[PDB]
Length: 107
Image 1 (spheres, rainbow, N blue to C red):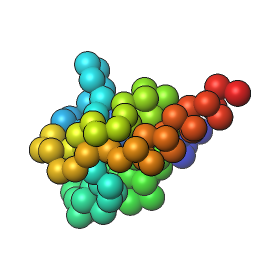
Image 2: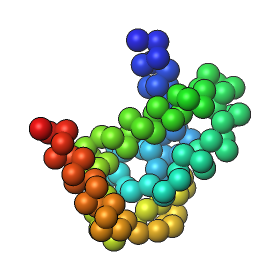
Image 3: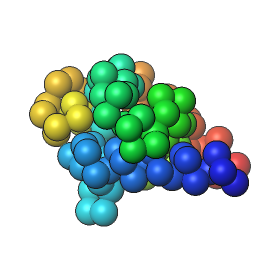
Image 4: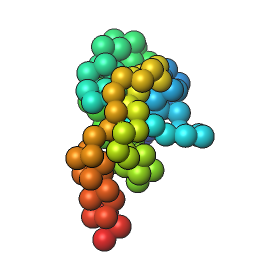
């Protein structure tokens, strides 16, 4: 319960500070491989408002396990950094891994 609200807080902090990556009100886009390391460079600012590094990791894990995120991992879609800049493209293997994950969760 407390850990859940702490995870939700981390997700709200991610959407407020990096909405290009984590504001999913209209769209969701593939994230850079290693986006977690980029987020953790901001850990000091997050901790001042009550968000720990481990809650930042839990929030990214929750965000990227959602089916709508897995569904956006299609071959040659663009991966973005925290500010929505294009950095790479989704590979066929990554797209296959994502669809396999979706099929497992609905079963």
